[PDB]
Length: 47
Length: 50
Ligand SMILES: *[C@@H]1O[C@H](CO)[C@@H](O)[C@H](O)[C@H]1NC(C)=O
Image (cartoon, rainbow over all chains, first blue to last red; front, side):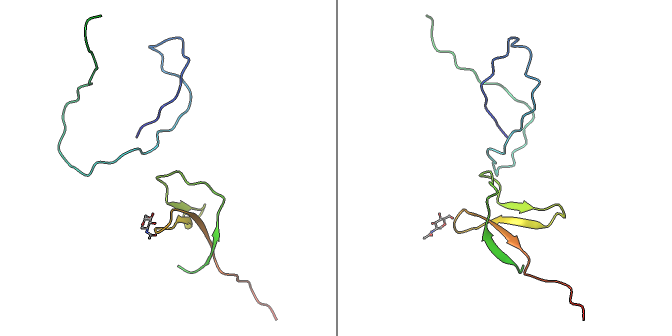
């Protein structure tokens, strides 16, 4: 269930205290047990 | 079910296909063939007094 918005919040640590709803985006029929989650980051080259 | 099928102005979100009323009875539907919003109204009825 995802949702994207533009936000102009001044404090990055502070998620906005505004009501919002997350529509059902996608469903996956596979039932593989999952225990742990790793965020994936994009990091290209020295600049 | 049995009823009168009409076009409905209620907007369904893309995932939504069915609509329900206060009584938790189906009030609107999305046609399986063409994705369109149709509401169902029961056929006309009324008490008869002599
Ligand atoms: C078959 O089903 C799809 C999904 O509703 C629909 O878009 C398509 O038009 C249908 N085929 C015909 C010939 O109507």
